Amino acid sequence: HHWGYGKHNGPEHWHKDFPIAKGERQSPVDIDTHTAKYDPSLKPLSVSYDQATSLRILNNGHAFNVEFDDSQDKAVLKGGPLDGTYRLIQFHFHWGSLDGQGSEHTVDKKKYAAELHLVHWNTKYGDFGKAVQQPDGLAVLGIFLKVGSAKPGLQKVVDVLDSIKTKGKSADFTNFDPRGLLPESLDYWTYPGSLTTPPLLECVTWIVLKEPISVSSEQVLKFRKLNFNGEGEPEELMVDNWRPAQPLKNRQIKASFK
Ligand SMILES: NS(=O)(=O)c1ccc(CCNC(=O)Nc2ccc(I)cc2)cc1
Ligand SMILES: [Zn+2]
């Protein structure tokens, strides 16, 4: 009876196995755009993805992860609110059953169709498993998806999903360039938070870009053909794999922009 996104094992149940679910810095949150304050001390974000080495795509039963070689400093995130160098390890998405829901963060209570998470770990902690035990261990770059024009740089991901339909399936996924998933502007909001899935560790500096990317209805329909189940189990479509907004508590969301 493992955690998931059903009526019986969904986000309102997670606190029984993971009591940090009711903690002081949980994610996601609603971004109240009027309450977020410009922080002129933040720096421009530095997204350095030219040497990124993708390896594999995995259906883990919760989402799909595009994994990177993080055994050297290739694809890194620096600057903004961050001290030091964070290495890209994987990206994944959260999405809805309908275009009106699917994001984890919200903006003035608006839900987007989906949300991309580019996950990075602080190199001063040596490995990803040590980094998740630290309050500044991870930096997750969050990007909203809205339905409209196709995102050409997403299509290579869309086209491999038939090969990882079910939980535990993986496929080789080399030479994928994550620069093709970024919007034009790197204007962002930032706040201290958590992983949005169990184990819900409070180890994330969240960096959420203001500018959504556009994907087509056909691209997101292909996400919704994935399965939560394993092969040879009853088909359960992988949709609504999002955690709703959590209390802000004693936190301030800072804006990089006026
Ligand atoms: N949605 S999100 O961006 O906030 C997000 C959710 C979850 C994760 C992965 C968490 N995995 C983990 O804690 N690692 C781990 C490693 C080694 C051992 I031994 C045990 C556990 C990444 C990003
Ligand atoms: Zn995520």
Image (cartoon, grey):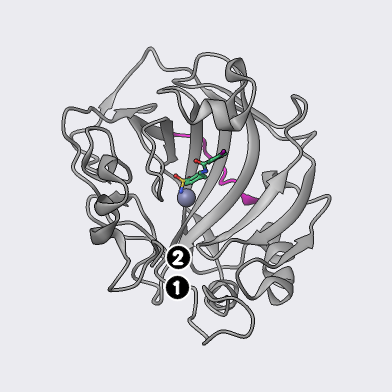
Main SS of the magenta part reads loop
Q: Position of residue 239 (x, y in %)?
A: 45, 73
Quadrant occupied by the C terminus: top left
Q: Can residue 29 be seen at all in this image of the molecule?
A: no
- Asked whether, in this view, residue 89 is left or right of residue 254, the answer is right
- Asked whether, in this view, residue 229 is left or right of residue 254, the answer is right
Q: Which residues are magenta?
A: 181-187
Q: Position of residue 54 (x, y in %)?
A: 77, 46
Q: Residue at x 44, y 23 (%)?
A: 134
Residue type pointed to by label 2 = Trp
Q: Residue at x 63, y 27 (%)?
A: 127
Q: From what the image shows, is residue 117 above or below residue 25? A: below
1 or 2: mark nearer the eye = 1
Numbered badge on residue 239:
1
Which is more toward the observer, 81 or 55?
55
Disc 1 + disc 2, Cβ < 8 Å: yes
Q: Residue at x 45, y 34 (%)?
A: 187
Q: Which residue is mark 2?
A: 95
Residue type pointed to by label 1 = Val
Please tell me whether mark 2 sits on a helix, a strand or a loop.
strand
Quadrant occupied by the N terminus: bottom left
